[PDB]
Amino acid sequence: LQRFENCGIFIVMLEVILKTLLRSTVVFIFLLLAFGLSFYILLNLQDPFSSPLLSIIQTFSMMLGDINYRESFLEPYLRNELAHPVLSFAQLVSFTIFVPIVLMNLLIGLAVGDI
Amino acid sequence: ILVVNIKPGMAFNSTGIINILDTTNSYLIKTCMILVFLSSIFGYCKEISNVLEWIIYTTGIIFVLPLFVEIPAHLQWQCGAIAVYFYWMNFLLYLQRFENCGIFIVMLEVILKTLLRSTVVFIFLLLAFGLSFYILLNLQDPFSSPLLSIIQTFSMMLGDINYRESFLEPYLRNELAHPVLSFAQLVSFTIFVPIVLMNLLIGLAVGDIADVQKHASLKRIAMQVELHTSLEKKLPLWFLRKVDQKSTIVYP
Amino acid sequence: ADVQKHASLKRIAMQVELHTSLEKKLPLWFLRKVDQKSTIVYP
Ligand SMILES: C[C@H]1[C@H](F)C[C@@H](C(=O)NCc2cc(-c3cnc(C(F)(F)F)nc3)ncc2C(F)(F)F)N1S(=O)(=O)c1ccc(F)cc1
Ligand SMILES: C[C@H]1[C@H](F)C[C@@H](C(=O)NCc2cc(-c3cnc(C(F)(F)F)nc3)ncc2C(F)(F)F)N1S(=O)(=O)c1ccc(F)cc1
Image (cartoon, rainbow over all chains, first blue to last red; front, side, top):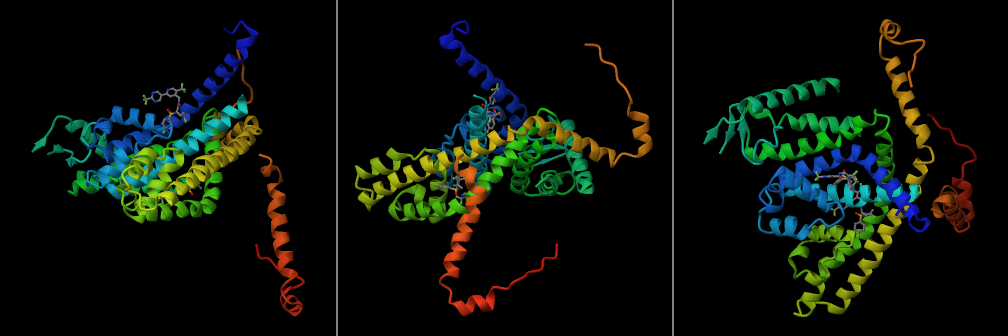
């Protein structure tokens, strides 16, 4: 579709943002790996974090701002199923600040700036 | 390597993993513990970057103290969850030396400081909802205590309000004590904080990252020049004369 | 991004409008007691 004037500029805008997002992972995958390996320690008794790979896929999927908060922090806390409660909520807010808010606004800053 | 080969919560020693004691990774666990311990005692001697290095080395020791001193399994992994996190968070602050990484850490430093100036104001906009939902929704598990109420009303700000599970399903069972005011506070939240504050933060984020990109093509080179001159101020002069070079050829 | 055009002036305009509103309403002898003509700084 790049060969039609009606289409090609939206694929220039896709090429430009996808390449920008790619340069950004060479830094921020080491941010994801901090949360993925940390929630593997803190939430290990739960199905959705049971293994380091599933924990990094979960913290990848939480990125968009859908943390499943009641289902894996609160309902476990009110049943003592959290092993490290004071630190587990401190890692919840550290994720919520750094990723759904800081990184996902940093990427709107890049995308709006480039497009 | 010491994390992913041991189930989190099990005590361990150089001899292996305790449940029973078993030896199936013992040479890997022994060598990784000695390497982390050495890295931490040398880490103190090389002593926000300066603060994170204390949090890492004072805690990565506690995760590995069972190389010498037996410790509660809970304290070993509660330290592991902190040390394993801050090792990777602080790895980004080493990436600033690479030409093509550092500008994204500059854009992270700028937006994080911009959000923190905005937090000194809007914590009181959170605490208004956090203590109001503590009154209006007290019969529900997520709002059972003022601290849990403020954690829940923090976590709602992304625009994930659990509306059916805490307003409408409770309303259709008369479990809301103050129904008219409870829905009036549900709208007042949905306006002020997943819409007005998050669109304000996107306004700050775009406005100041599009200003880093105004200088980025110079900031790359200014970081490199300040790095290489800092090393010329710290390398001994004979080494610079042996290693530096007056002319170079290129073959395109 | 338009408030951030004026922000570095708007900080000061808010401070000037605050301090001049108080300077109109504190009683005249109080300003003459308090409003010192020079100040030193030690960097
Ligand atoms: C660069 C940042 C942004 F801020 C947001 C996010 C992103 O959308 N990046 C695109 C991307 C992802 C992956 C990928 C593949 N597979 C996994 C695994 F292992 F989990 F399965 N993870 C990531 N590969 C290539 C790309 C690229 F081509 F687009 F560049 N990333 S982040 O670093 O992943 C990330 C950061 C924080 C966080 F909390 C969670 C994740
Ligand atoms: C400044 C505003 C933004 F618009 C959005 C949001 C945010 O992401 N700020 C980052 C942040 C949060 C916390 C924090 C820690 N711990 C709790 C507690 F008590 F709940 F556990 N709450 C907050 N600390 C430091 C930072 C900072 F360093 F980044 F600045 N905040 S807000 O004020 O919190 C907030 C506002 C409205 C709302 F409806 C809910 C919350």
